[PDB]
Image (cartoon, coloured by chain):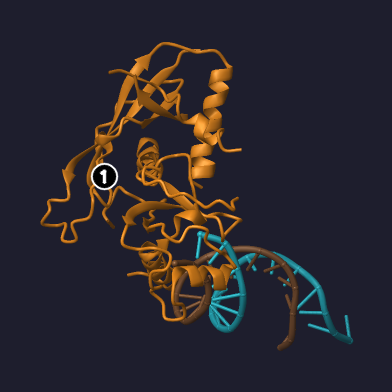
Chain colours: A orange, B cyan, C brown
Amino acid sequence: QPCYLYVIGMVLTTPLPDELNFRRRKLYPPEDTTRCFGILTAKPIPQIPHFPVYTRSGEVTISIELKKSGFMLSLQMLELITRLHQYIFSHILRYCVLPLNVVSTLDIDFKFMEDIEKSETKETPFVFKLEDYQDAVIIPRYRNFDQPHRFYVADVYTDLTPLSKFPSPEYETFAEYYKTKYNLDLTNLNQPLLDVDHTSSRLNLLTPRPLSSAEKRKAKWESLQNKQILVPELCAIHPIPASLWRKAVCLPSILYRLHC
RNA sequence: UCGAAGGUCCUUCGUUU
RNA sequence: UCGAAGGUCCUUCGUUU
């Protein structure tokens, strides 16, 4: 069985021009990170011209490039990749797609699978490690247990602490809000707080980067969602880093282009 | 994100002697 | 006339910190 291994090139050719960025938000170039995604096929791919996807950070050019050709490796490895492809499309999102990393040539990511398979308290308190949350996706443990919500860590607010003033009038402090509503007590009252961002699955080929009722309401919801400030002790860190996650959310748009 | 309700129209069927 | 089952779209609301 002949195999063909493609890499999905992501390079930011047109960053926000810095006139267009009024708010001077951080830019997240895809080329700054070595971990990417590839497509695995049986029959090769009919050459596709390179195309843009429009993200918050700018115009990102997608190039489908052939990294390796003609090989094949076992069956169990062929079967394992499928579990990652599912994981990407079922658990992360909602012929084969797999993670790659640098060795200056590219191979299948060795550190991907065991973060997840690494994931199978307390009286002495939660400890805040700044390097944990640097590139991170966090989920709140205290709500939405069915389908947990996930956020990028946008900022670490260092002057803020769980005893800082809660933004809404009904509560004095974050400590109080979480105690009152969720019955949660914090073991660490000196920890900073986290700013978040969220995007997930939409179409990136055009630039939203006449609304109905159901959509005008999600506009407000998404808006408030991004203004949320979260508590690190009350949040779990997702194994897949935010940097790889940002590449992952372009996959539906990119795979759409290859089909059409 | 997950839900709730009101309305509107369409499809399929029941209902009379 | 009164109903059943399924769907479409519009509108209103809850849900986050």
Q: Position of residue C5 (x, y in %)?
A: 72, 67
Q: Quadrant of the C terminus of chain A?
A: top left
Residue A149 visible at all: no
Q: Residue at x 35, y 45 (%)?
A: A134
- Relative placement, left or right, of B10 versus A221 is right
Q: Quadrant of residue A220?
A: bottom left
Instruction: Using the image as rendered, state which of residue A210 and residue A64 is in the foreground.
Output: A64
Res. A207 image quadrant: bottom left
Q: Number of callouts in the render?
A: 1
Is residue A108 positioned above or below A27 on the image? Answer: above
Q: Position of residue A63 (x, y in %)?
A: 27, 31
Against A19, residue A3 (above or below) is above
Q: Chain of mark 1?
A: A
- Report whether A85 appears left or right of A245: right
Give the side of residue B13 with respect to residue B5, left or right: right
Residue at the extreme front = A124
**Which of the pair A195/A84 is nearer the observer?**
A195
Q: Picture coordinates of residue A174 (x, y %)?
A: 45, 69
Q: Is residue A21 above or below residue A242?
A: below
For disc 1, the neighbor class at 10 Å (few under 14, some 14 to 19, many from 20) is some
Residue nearer the viewer, A120 or A90: A120
x, y percent for residue A166: 41, 73
Please give the residue where the numbered disc 1 appears in the rendered image. Answer: A28
Whether residue A66 can be seen here: yes
Badge 1 element: loop
Residue found 32% across the figure and 49% down from its top: A204
| Residue at screen point 57% across, 38% down | A119
Tell me the amino acid under the disc marked 1. Answer: Tyr
